[PDB]
Amino acid sequence: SLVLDQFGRNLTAAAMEGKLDPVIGREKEIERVMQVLSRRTKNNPVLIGEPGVGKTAVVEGLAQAIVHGEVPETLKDKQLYTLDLGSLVAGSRYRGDFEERLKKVLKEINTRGDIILFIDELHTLVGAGAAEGAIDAASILKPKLARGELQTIGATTLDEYRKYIEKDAALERRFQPVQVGEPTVEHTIEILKGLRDRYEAHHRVSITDAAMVAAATLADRYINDRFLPDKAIDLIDEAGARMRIRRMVAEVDDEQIAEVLGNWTGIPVFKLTEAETTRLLRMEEELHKRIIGQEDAVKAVSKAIRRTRAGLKDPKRPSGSFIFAGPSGVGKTELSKALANFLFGDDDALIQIDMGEFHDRFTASRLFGAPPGYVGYEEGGQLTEKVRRKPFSVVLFDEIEKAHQEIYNSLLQVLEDGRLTDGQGRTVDFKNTVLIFTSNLGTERMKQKVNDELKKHFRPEFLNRIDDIIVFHQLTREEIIRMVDLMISRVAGQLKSKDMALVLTDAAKALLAKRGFDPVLGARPLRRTIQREIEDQLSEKILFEEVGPGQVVTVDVDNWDGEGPGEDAVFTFT
Amino acid sequence: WTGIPVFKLTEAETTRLLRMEEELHKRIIGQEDAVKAVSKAIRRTRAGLKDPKRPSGSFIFAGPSGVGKTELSKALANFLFGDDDALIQIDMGEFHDRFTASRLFGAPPGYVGYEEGGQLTEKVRRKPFSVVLFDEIEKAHQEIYNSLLQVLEDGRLTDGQGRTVDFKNTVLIFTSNLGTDYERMKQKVNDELKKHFRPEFLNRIDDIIVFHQLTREEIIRMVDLMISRVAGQLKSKDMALVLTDAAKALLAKRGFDPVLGARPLRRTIQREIEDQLSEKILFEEVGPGQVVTVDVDNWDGEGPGEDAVFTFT
Amino acid sequence: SLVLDQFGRNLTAAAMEGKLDPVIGREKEIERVMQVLSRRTKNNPVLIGEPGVGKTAVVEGLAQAIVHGEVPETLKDKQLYTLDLGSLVAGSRYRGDFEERLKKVLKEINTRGDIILFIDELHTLVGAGAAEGAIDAASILKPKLARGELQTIGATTLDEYRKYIEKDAALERRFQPVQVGEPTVEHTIEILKGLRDRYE
Ligand SMILES: Nc1ncnc2c1ncn2[C@@H]1O[C@H](COP(=O)(O)OP(=O)(O)O)[C@@H](O)[C@H]1O
Ligand SMILES: Nc1ncnc2c1ncn2[C@@H]1O[C@H](COP(=O)(O)OP(=O)(O)O)[C@@H](O)[C@H]1O
Ligand SMILES: Nc1ncnc2c1ncn2[C@@H]1O[C@H](COP(=O)(O)OP(=O)(O)O)[C@@H](O)[C@H]1O
Ligand SMILES: Nc1ncnc2c1ncn2[C@@H]1O[C@H](COP(=O)(O)OP(=O)(O)O)[C@@H](O)[C@H]1O
């Protein structure tokens, strides 16, 4: 007892005082472990599982089963000791110290005979006192473990089992695997219901059953870098901590779990208040604050985001996938910029990928990285990593028709299931991101021309996965008048920072409108008209210090009937 | 230990294995040939009467888009393991480049990522009994099939690290989209597969299955199948939806097109029911504790219904 | 304290003399850190932030909050020590010296219980001294982090996180990411107004 205690911790006395958490739902794996230790030769199981499933929890539950007495006679009255390799290695300046300590431990185990050894993180045994080919813990344990005279229990994750143990086939032979599979949703709910009491006592808060059901569902659905039941426990524990901080008896509901998840991952799953609800209902006007015209596209996107925010989106598919195909300059990109501004408050959050560069057969690997064995393997994908930074995003694929079919064959993955496997092998989540595909093709009859061009330039499946195909309409006179108003407002807002005030009469706005209309319009022209007839004149006029700072500038027009072409009209800057 | 299901067939398991054709028909409407072939393969595998060298099953699936080729594999995984996420899904859409194939089995020694190993081989070693799905196999280059060439016949793959993995107990499924009256389509699909793939690869596969186009009965049952998802989603918010049969008829009328598969129907449902119900929910017109009876007015049930709308109660 | 002063620096004692710059406008991140540090199991936050944003600034603000006493009861009068891994593995020359120093540090922390660790460049835990016969500090720390018996705070670049901690999922599990994003323009102006007195 005195020898093992300085080099290990006894889980039996830990479960005597209840210091270990109760373990429930693990009868199959614990029975598997108990039946492996009841063998004659090679009675050593190692718990292989994905990290965060309960590999140490299985051993704690077995210790509780031992101390209660549900074990058979082969595991009855057995003190389960974990072994700390760090305590063995530390303090050993010399060969004799470490090997003497390990063999004294083994002699005490074989003398008392009722200590089952536990090696958490079993991959540490390949090299303890020296390298893999010298005298260490593994080469001392191997003759003992081969005959089964030393009962030990291991725990190693999947990847480290592949890496460290499997390169040492001698230890791989002597350990019989016990797979601890990831628990289900109902299993996680049961586990949380079991662990209610400890967290309730610790955080001085009370937790409801609906809170735990919501925690399990949200943790399984959204968080895709951790594994059940750890993420559900994380959400519950963090909500309890939030209540403990905020009160300094509180209640935890699913709303607080949603808040914790929103803090953790940024996914906008919240209980909607009145102000954001009226914002969501009236957001078509909010988008129409910036974009002018094109009611169909804003309507479709409003429908998609309203469906997403109300919990009515198919969870295996993204929030929405759109093809914005229409004549150049209409505002296909500006709709995406307006979406970014609405959803995040800033426009730099729009992950914009340009398909102009992806015209070669070698550049498809930029999105999802390079395969193993090639240059760029560690960096991985550019798009996948950008998505992993923030799971809720608007992904913009600008100028689709430039890129050729290999990228779309890559993107059928995300268009169907919202998954993408980068070069490093990891799968990333796209179940919440909004996909926008902007195209410049086909330039009521324009609708059919664009549809025919897209059917000719695409395979049927890629057009089929897309939620809504939206064809942008050409602009009219009222829309370009409002565009002129918006551009002048932008100029005035930029000029506010230089101690200025700017204003235009409606005659100047009309004159700008009459010189900015043709079927090849958009905002690429009629903004060049602004830069040529307003901005340039203002710059040259303020460079030689007339109507400088503190002076309101009024842009007027003379020699114009207000209806004519206005080619002889000139802008006057008072 | 290994998870490979060799046991004594209990009566419940036996009567399930006799009746698993309609169990597959629970999630797939129509496509009797593919369900037939999958049932034959699973019956051969679980009876203990199987070729030791060849894999459990090797199928190539062909048909139009959205005829349930991936849905069949997902429902087969749901049958065997209980959930879709146990399906080992490798989509060949990322493997267009010839240099990309090293991700499948792994990096050779002396190169970066050698210690990481492959992706397909390691996931097969994790679960030796698995349904391996290869989506859109034509979109990968032809040199990628060369790695699968020997697992399709001998069921063994040699990774970069040198280990030999066992593909003997897995069900290999290929899904294609080539070819896009039934016999003419089958002949065209077979000819396209023959001229697209080398004949030494087509001979090593078990059955070539062509998916039949969806008919009116199939899509009108599939209306129910895909609205059950919305009903279950609504059940999480303490409110229920029941469709009038007129709503089902109108949804099946506006979502049917022989040119494509099932996703036009999902578009029709999503635009007619999901979006409008989202507006009604966020307006708080309807909430928890109520029922929603969706009905079609201004319609006769036979006409095309270019003016019919949906009423929500 | 006799062993930690040889290997670490006391930020609470540093905040006693006000040698740390005032931290302005980072109340949300400090609240998130105190939220994570208040948990029962896995109470280790990592400040996942781009370089140049103030990852260490968040920790010094937390130390100033602790010394000013506005923290909740679960962080009241707890000395926040930064852990200098270079000094821990500085004089070893052997196989058992570094692990002995780590055991002494952890035993002093356990017998005190009011000391929170801070690890600049948290990715240095993996491979924190790995000779032919040595066990790195990550494998020592992992059982204590999983049970929640040790409160550690980490600061790590996004890219460094992805290169190093992402490769080790066992240690990645024990740390909750805390997104520290770039301050906006107005936030930068507020920070400059805070730092006016010191720079003047
Ligand atoms: N059946 C269960 N009952 C109670 N708690 C559980 C159960 N399964 C898992 N847990 C919790 O999840 C955690 C699992 O940790 P574990 O997976 O052993 O870590 P590692 O993967 O590093 O070995 C434990 O802290 C435990 O509290
Ligand atoms: N209706 C509009 N409202 C506001 N800005 C617009 C509008 N239409 C165009 N713009 C501006 O003009 C640009 C046109 O972009 P876009 O239509 O995407 O060009 P293209 O169609 O050639 O890709 C946008 O970046 C936007 O700033
Ligand atoms: N017969 C069917 N029964 C139910 N759903 C179907 C059926 N056919 C297609 N689907 C729908 O189509 C999608 C799968 O289509 P898929 O088989 O992947 O087509 P492809 O393989 O050509 O891409 C699923 O989301 C499913 O909802
Ligand atoms: N909110 C803030 N208030 C005051 N100073 C800040 C704030 N945020 C950042 N700083 C300044 O930024 C610097 C911190 O950078 P640091 O986090 O050390 O970068 P890195 O961790 O990459 O070395 C400090 O000098 C600090 O003064």
Image (cartoon, coloured by chain):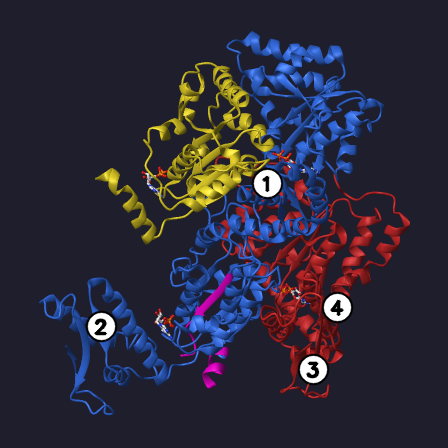
Outermost residue toward the left?
A544
Picture coordinates of residue A315, whole percent (x, y):
62, 59
Residue denoted by label 2: A502
- In the image, the chain rendered in red is B
The color chain C is rendered in: yellow
Picture coordinates of residue B234, whole percent (x, y):
68, 64
The span from disc 4 to disc 3 (Cα, nearest Å) is 25 Å
Question: Of the residues under marks 4 and 3, which one precedes in the sequence?
Answer: 4
Q: Could you tell me the amino acid type at mark 3? A: Val
Respond whether the residues carrying marks 2 and 3 are from the same subunit.
Answer: no
The span from disc 2 to disc 1 (Cα, nearest Å) is 70 Å
Q: Looking at the image, which is closer to me, C63 or B98?
A: C63
Q: Quadrant of residue B67?
A: bottom right
Outermost residue toward the top?
A96
Question: Is residue A376 visible to the viewer in this orientation of the structure?
Answer: no
Residue denoted by label 4: B29
- Residue B24 is left or right of residue A272, and the answer is right
Residue denoted by label 1: B159
Evaluate if marks 4 and 1 touch, with contact meaning CB atoms under 8 Å apart: no
Q: Could you tell me the amino acid type at mark 1? A: Asp
Q: Image point 44% across, 31% down: which residue?
A: C119
Checking the image for residue B171, the label placed there is: none
- Residue A5 is left or right of residue A483, and the answer is right
Output the chain of dot 3.
B
Q: Is mark 4 within 8 Å of ligand 3?
A: yes
Q: Could you tell me the amino acid type at mark 4? A: Ile
The region drawn magenta spans A434-451
Evaluate if marks 4 and 3 touch, with contact meaning CB atoms under 8 Å apart: no
Question: Is residue C90 visible to the viewer in this orientation of the structure?
Answer: yes
